[PDB]
Image (cartoon, coloured by chain):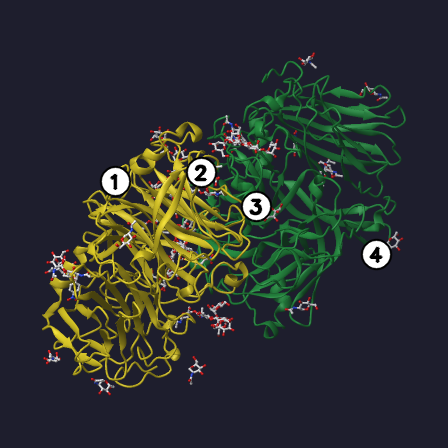
Chain colours: A green, B yellow
């Protein structure tokens, strides 16, 4: 095939394996060296302060299978180094009857077996596995392994009675799933349960949730408690923590709860970050983050959600997490968010961005699939002095409201997300930074106005503050990865409250997805203000477009323009007039970002392989 | 429990694990250090002249499961040393999706991958597996591994296309089984196929059989040929080598062909041992040895058989092995015979002797199950100058006859088996040998006459030649493991041609088997003789009783007397009179035999373990 990016693309399906390896590939973020990746796993801050990140991995293939933990480490979330051992960059792989079908997601007990960091993970064996299939007990169990070398290798507990797997009995019949154990400490839950520990005999300092659901009756998050402090074999089932209905939706701001949960976690946050109080901090909020499946017509039937919850203690010594309000962690092509504690009272979240090639047309030509999102600090976002005339404000859909004593202003609380400052500092410092003059978008505004400085490649960031009239019908935003013939348009339309990514012209290559992305964004109007403001930040990284609005709304998507010069960026304006003006300020472009994998050459493909005719016989993995 | 062997046994089911480890345990033969063992596998003579023996092994359990290769070596078939590596005495174990359900039987390519000894073995995965179940393609495949350290460890080929497993497609639909690859070189088969290699393109110097059958339509031995010399991935299916009918029997001397073959092998022998001619040696005979299942009402539904065959070349470049005559390799509690070449033009065979505790009542108390037989030289047994008035002679059931030119005498040919001379020499040399005076059994003979010298423990051998009148109705034999209250009786009754082992009084412990064993023995009468002779040799080794008659008939069984003094032996006589006399000569007792595992302590138990509740969930292994 021809790789001439100055002319229209040919038939790229004729290209060899990994011939398009560098063409669309992110450079400034976490990604496997090659092949298939999906969910983050095994995330923890090591004793030396560095971050260990695992991920679901299938090297030398471009579909899921033999799923293993690949791993790497970083001192700043931003520049990474691969582990290299006897299995390359893998550190846990299928090896025993109980996990031979896949080492699924798992999470870290920092002070575990013999004092070592310990992973509790879903060990899978044979049989139908899935929320739409007739799964049986044993197919998904939960197992332990520990590391004596800070994540370079893991030792599994032995197979058998009183050893691995450590959790195998289904807590209810007819489960849709039983996976993704999330281990956490919780002074809050310990305080709530302290008066009931005689009922259950579970007194350990670690809790674990397991994600699943019940056939025909919606998703479930099951809560376990470590039976005894310092002992890791026995985990006592308390009860369902979160119970939702079959394809239940809390509404337009909240996705859909589907039929089954995946990768659920539990945290507690306050306005500064992570909160480790027992309930005494009145500014702190309990949150659950979770994926749902089969409640969405597109995006691989997957919603990455979160909910604020109020805990109630049941008479049998378990906890009901009652949903107070419910939102979306990312509105685009991402899923499988994991969060973990970081020193300085932080909780950091990261997810997986899948490709937009669902028919698997150019995956072999790429030689890889998937990347992470950026790493995000979670916190309680608080907006003070909100005007009660903010449209829709008292729906309290994915936020809560608290009136002032006099009823004239409102305090809004919701989940905040922002890129970790280490990454922003490194990006800015390594980039060519252009601080741009403010622009009034009025009757003279073109549909597209290129920035006065332009990117030089597909690795850049941009930010801007868009000030709108309170009754505007104008739209504005950013165009990125743009030439005359290919471009991706990011619009906000305050009248509809919709942030969209229009991808009809994103690429000349017709096999990639081109559906319009959509997020809801609430501009909380401030008392006394005669305008409302959207702070919009965009990261462009190969084919990833990752959008953040108001440290609250995130939308990750993909664009694969063919032409070498489809790298431009600028401002979008629609329906701006002399009377309906959009003021854009705080404009800045960072060109270049950071080389996130400095030790890797440009092409880390090792080729692709086929599992052969037995893949279809076993029926577990696609085989390629 | 009480282990007082001077009084009646108590309730031994109350005894702890491995508390009866030494009580009944063989000392003079090949046996695992502890736990479950079954079939011999991976047998070969190493470059240094020593013998490598593998076996199906499940350490720390007393039922089958996670089946692996345990291994040991010997310079004389008799004194053995265990391998000791990272997995103890195991050297191959389930580790990959293709073999995670068990590393089943396999055999050796001496000059294989990169010139190293290479095993071709049955790699098993998930799904129904068995001749009475609905097995599917993929559940049993055939895979390669090689050793760079003379059997201390094995490296498997990688999983995938053009790698492991190397044989996976079923040659016919609806197989009852597809396992136990037997690799061999054959100048005979090469010569037969040389004119047809254009039809199949298979020209390699190794052949392999795979054992199985077809549902409802009997057993099958499938023949493959290595496609190209020096290359080990591609094996071409030629056709069925042996085809038998559903529960077909050739008769009383020949067991039953059942529904499915296991552990089948192919060899060529002459009167001296192994024959490596191309067909030019007129004294050589082609043989197949094979196990059959579900054609027997007892003995675990298993027959260990052999057949002499005449090869025919089919038009499609395959071989039909037409059965000429058909016999039994061992008439007792043994199965899974494997044979292998040994320097000096020898073919040596060894099998597995199972316990007689089929309800698994005292297996945990033993802490082990199973042993090998002794190692046996195979050869063509030729008897000259046989009288045509030998009863039943021209049935030619498990032998062939060739008349002299004048029709007055017959040459008889059959399969010969004898204990390897290395073992007999070592046994005799380490024993207290008593050469006993000949005994005429007549009207004065007691039912039981103790030998003039007695054994001192349960480890001894005895031999004798019993001369009978041509029209005798007398019976005689040996009693072993004998006190007043417990004993095992080995009888030959020339009038019925039956060799029996009567075990009604073998033990005071009622849970062990007590059924009478039976073999057919043909005393070929010699021209001019006025008598007929049975040469009977018996090895007593813990609980094993292994009987050989006339270097032809073998019968392995088990006896578990409780009393410490149930060790005696002597002569049996029934219906001997002044006129019907049995002359016994060549009588000799070897007391002690050899310590076959000199580096092992008396108790090599490591305890027993339970796999836990997941064993029943996975449904593959009993779990204990
Ligand atoms: C079917 O059969 C399968 C095969 O048998 C079976 O799988 C095997 O299961 C067994 C049993 O569970 C596993 O055995 C365990 O192994 C653990 C260590 O595992 C790691 O290391 C081994 C060995 O590594 C050596 O060899 C390899 C290979 O050559 C080398 O690469 C290594 O470098 C290393 O080499 C050195 O050592 C060799 C000899 O050992 C030398 O020959 C060599 O020269 C070198 O010097 C690896 O093989 C393992 O790899 C495999 O597993 C990993 C995942 O873990 C995979 O990723 C990988 O691909 C492989 O598959 C692995 O790296 C042991 O720790 C463990 O022993 C502990 O537990 C048992 C009980 O379960 C105790 O009896 C024992 O005492 C140990 O417990 C003590 O120690 C720990 C801390 O160390 C404590 O937590 C514990 O409390 C206890 O303490 C006690 O003692 C203390 C005294 O110090 C005292 O203070 C305490 O108070 C207390 O009393 C166990 O041996 C085996 O690994 C499996 N093998 C494989 C290949 O899978 C499978 O399950 C079966 N399936 C079924 C269904 O039945
Ligand atoms: C799901 O994922 C699973 C995990 O990824 C996956 O299983 C893995 O599959 C891969 C791919 O098939 C296997 O990789 C192969 O490994 C073979 C060696 O295997 C043995 O050794 C390894 C490594 O041993 C080191 O590490 C262990 C663990 O720490 C130590 O115990 C050892 O002591 C040793 O340690 C040293 O080295 C380390 C680094 O390597 C150092 O860190 C350390 O300090 C030490 O110095 C073991 O791990 C293996 O154990 C496992 O497997 C055994 C059974 O085999 C089990 O019993 C055991 O329990 C474990 O499970 C094992 O002992 C390699 O030989 C092989 O590489 C060859 O093939 C590939 C292609 O397939 C070629 O690319 C490569 O070039 C090699 O081929 C050349 O060499 C051979 C001869 O050596 C030739 O025959 C061949 O023609 C070719 O020659 C070429 O080069 C020549 C130049 O010299 C030239 O002359 C020729 O012309 C030609 O060009 C391959 O790497 C891996 O072992 C599996 N791992 C496990 C744990 O199972 C699984 O399949 C997946 N499942 C699915 C469904 O997808
Ligand atoms: C001697 O060797 C055995 C191995 O053979 C060692 O382990 C024991 O194995 C036997 C099987 O041989 C197991 O028996 C089965 O037990 C289950 C129920 O077990 C539960 O209750 C037990 C009694 O208090 C308890 O000990 C068990 O605890 C272990 O297992 C749990 C996991 O469940 C684990 O968390 C613990 O830490 C322990 O490891 C467990 O709670 C029973 O259902 C089985 O019944 C079947 O079989 C019987 C007998 O034929 C039959 O009557 C039933 O109808 C049914 O068909 C079976 O009894 C035993 O549990 C194992 N014990 C263990 C692991 O401690 C044993 O330890 C060795 N002894 C010594 C001293 O070393
Ligand atoms: C590029 O990367 C791929 C891995 O993705 C490398 O391997 C090839 O993978 C593809 C799948 O991506 C395989 O395609 C399938 O092939 C089978 C039929 O294969 C047979 O015929 C082939 C053509 O001549 C031949 O090459 C194969 O030989 C290999 O495998 C045998 C074992 O069977 C082995 O013994 C050999 O040594 C070889 O290793 C084999 O004989 C086909 O049935 C599949 O069809 C399905 O999918 C297609 C596509 O969607 C669809 O149209 C069908 O309807 C059906 O659903 C599929 O085409 C391919 O066989 C693999 N090739 C190999 C292993 O050589 C590939 O090698 C990499 N290229 C390079 C240059 O590195
Ligand atoms: C948009 O971003 C601006 C700039 O960061 C935010 O304004 C700042 O608000 C903080 C208080 O939290 C002040 O300390 C700064 O001085 C403000 N800077 C200004 C006004 O330039 C603004 O709050 C953001 N708006 C939204 C809606 O998120
Ligand atoms: C029983 O054993 C005896 C002793 O080994 C066998 O008799 C020997 O036969 C060989 C010929 O093959 C002679 O060289 C020996 O001298 C014979 N010894 C004798 C008669 O004492 C005898 O053939 C065996 N009989 C059977 C039926 O197997
Ligand atoms: C970019 O490339 C295309 C195709 O080579 C060309 O037509 C166009 O003029 C170039 N420059 C742009 C769009 O600014
Ligand atoms: C505790 O009660 C809740 C609510 O009825 C129930 O769902 C849960 O299963 C119970 N926990 C147990 C039985 O451990
Ligand atoms: C909150 O304030 C709004 C606006 O003043 C008012 O309509 C509403 O009733 C108030 N809610 C409460 C609980 O006082
Ligand atoms: C550039 O990036 C590296 C890697 O993250 C970072 O450590 C470094 O501080 C950055 N350089 C700057 C900020 O000048
Ligand atoms: C309208 O927009 C253009 C471009 O920003 C600017 O030059 C002009 O001053 C604006 N008009 C007013 C009245 O500010
Ligand atoms: C052997 O032991 C039993 C039981 O202790 C005893 O009755 C008998 O007399 C002993 N001696 C024999 C049978 O020669
Ligand atoms: C032997 O003990 C077992 C328990 O292992 C008991 O069930 C059985 O009834 C006992 N047999 C007796 C007393 O005969
Ligand atoms: C060769 O012919 C025999 C007899 O018909 C048949 O059983 C066998 O399958 C054939 N071999 C092939 C098709 O490879
Ligand atoms: C073989 O010899 C027996 C006895 O003399 C005779 O009955 C039979 O017919 C002979 N067979 C042949 C083929 O000559
Ligand atoms: C005793 O047994 C050993 C082990 O087989 C053997 O090598 C040795 O030669 C024997 N001793 C003799 C025959 O005196
Ligand atoms: C009968 O048998 C006994 C014991 O062997 C012996 O003493 C006696 O001589 C035998 N009788 C004859 C006639 O040989
Ligand atoms: O790769 C398997 C893993 O990916 C997920 O399905 C999320 O997409 C998890 O539930 C599971 O552990
Ligand atoms: O342990 C499994 C092995 O044992 C046998 O069933 C014979 O009894 C073989 O066919 C198989 O390879
Ligand atoms: O791209 N940019 O100029 C940016 C991006 C992010 C940010 O927080 C500030 C500026
Ligand atoms: O499939 N199985 O459970 C088996 C197969 C063969 C055997 O010898 C024992 C058990
Ligand atoms: O026990 N014995 O005296 C024997 C056993 C076997 C043998 O070949 C000769 C004598």
User: CA gap, disc 3 to disc 1?
Assistant: 46 Å
Q: Which residue is mark 3?
A: A620
- Between label 3 and label 1, give the one nearer the viewer: 1
- Between label 2 and label 3, give the one nearer the viewer: 2
Please determine whether, in this image, residue B105 is positioned above or below residue A419.
Answer: below
Label 3 in the same subunit as label 1: no
Dots 1, 2 in contact, CB < 8 A? no
> Chain ID for label 1?
B
User: CA gap, disc 1 to disc 2?
Assistant: 23 Å
The C terminus of chain A sits in image quarter: top right
Q: Which residue is mark 1?
A: B276
> Chain ID for label 2?
B
Point out residue A331 in the picture as x, y percentages from the top left corner: 72, 40
Point out residue B467 in the picture as x, y percentages from the top left corner: 17, 69
Label 1 in the same subunit as label 2: yes
Point out residue B172 in the picture as x, y percentages from the top left corner: 51, 43
Q: Which residue is mark 4?
A: A405
User: CA gap, disc 2 to disc 4?
Assistant: 88 Å
Quadrant of residue B535 within the rendered picture: bottom left
User: CA gap, disc 2 to disc 3?
Assistant: 27 Å
Q: Is mark 2 within 8 Å of ligand 14?
A: yes
SS class, disc 3:
loop
Which dot marks residue B237?
Answer: 2
Mark nearer the N terminus (1 vs 2): 2
SS class, disc 1:
loop
> Chain ID for label 3?
A
- Between label 3 and label 4, give the one nearer the viewer: 3
């Amino acid at each position: 095939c021809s790789l001439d990016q100055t002319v229209a693309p040919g038939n790229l399906t004729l290209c060899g394996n990994a011939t398009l390896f560098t063409t669309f590939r992110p450079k400034a973020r976490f990604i496997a060296p090659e092949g298939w990746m999906n969910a983050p796993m095994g995330l923890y801050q090591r004793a030396d302060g560095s971050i260990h990140a695992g991920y679901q991995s299938h090297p030398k293939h471009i579909q899921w299978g033999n799923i293993s933990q690949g791993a790497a480490y970083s001192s700043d979330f931003t520049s990474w180094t691969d582990f290299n051992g006897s299995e390359g960059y893998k550190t846990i792989w299928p090896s025993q009857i109980y996990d031979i079908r896949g080492v699924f997601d798992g999470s870290i007990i920092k002070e575990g077996i013999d004092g070592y960091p310990t992973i509790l993970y879903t060990s899978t064996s044979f049989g139908p596995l899935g929320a739409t299939l007739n799964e049986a007990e044993g197919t998904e169990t939960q197992s332990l392994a520990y590391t004596t070398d800070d994540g370079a290798s893991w030792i599994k507990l032995g197979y058998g009675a009183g050893q691995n797997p450590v959790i195998y009995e289904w807590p209810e019949t007819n489960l849709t799933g039983f996976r993704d154990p999330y281990v956490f400490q919780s002074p809050r839950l310990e305080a709530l349960l302290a008066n009931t520990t005689s009922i259950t005999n579970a007194t350990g300092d670690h809790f674990a949730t397991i994600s699943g659901g019940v056939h025909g009756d919606g998703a479930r998050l099951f809560l376990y408690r470590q039976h005894t402090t310092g002992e890791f074999i026995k985990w006592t089932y308390l009860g369902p923590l979160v119970t939702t209905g079959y394809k239940e939706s809390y509404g337009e701001w909240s996705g859909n709860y589907g039929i089954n949960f995946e990768t659920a976690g539990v945290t507690r946050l306050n306005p500064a970050g992570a909160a480790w109080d027992n309930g005494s901090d009145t500014t702190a909020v309990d949150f659950v983050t979770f994926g749902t499946e089969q409640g969405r017509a597109d995006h691989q039937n997957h919603w990455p959600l979160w909910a604020a919850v109020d805990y109630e203690v049941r008479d049998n010594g378990s906890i009901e997490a009652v949903i107070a309000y419910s939102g979306v962690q990312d509105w685009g092509r991402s899923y499988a968010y994991a969060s973990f504690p970081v020193e300085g009272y932080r909780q950091v979240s990261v997810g997986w961005i899948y490709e937009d090639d669902d028919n698997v047309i150019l995956a072999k030509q790429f030689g890889y699939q998937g990347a992470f999102t950026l790493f995000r600090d979670l916190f309680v976002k608080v907006v003070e002095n909100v005007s009660p005339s903010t449209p829709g404000l008292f729906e309290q859909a994915s936020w809560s409201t608290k009136n002032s004593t006099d009823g004239m202003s409102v305090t809004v609380t919701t989940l905040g997300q922002r890129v970790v400052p280490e990454t922003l500092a490194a990006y800015k410092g390594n980039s060519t930074v252009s601080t741009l003059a403010p622009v009034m978008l009025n009757e003279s505004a073109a549909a597209y106005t290129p920035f006065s400085s332009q990117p030089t490649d597909r690795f850049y960031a941009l930010t801007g503050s868009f000030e709108f009239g309170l009754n505007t019908t104008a739209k504005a935003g950013f165009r990125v990865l743009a030439s005359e013939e290919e471009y991706t348009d990011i619009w906000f339309d305050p009248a509809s409250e919709n942030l969209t990514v229009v991808r009809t012209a994103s690429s000349l290559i017709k096999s990639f997805g081109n559906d319009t992305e959509l997020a809801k964004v609430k501009l909380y109007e401030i008392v006394g203000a005669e305008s409302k403001t959207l702070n919009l930040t965009v990261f462009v990284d190969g084919s990833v477009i990752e959008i953040y609005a108001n440290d609250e709304v995130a939308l990750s998507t993909r664009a694969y323009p063919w032409l070498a010069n489809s790298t431009g960026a600028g401002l979008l304006a629609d329906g701006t007039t002399a009377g309906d003006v959009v003021g854009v300020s705080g404009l800045e472009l960072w060109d270049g970002l950071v080389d996130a994998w400095p030790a890797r050459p440009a092409n880390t493909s090792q080729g692709l392989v086929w599992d052969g005719p037995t893949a279809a016989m076993y029926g577990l993995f696609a085989g390629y």
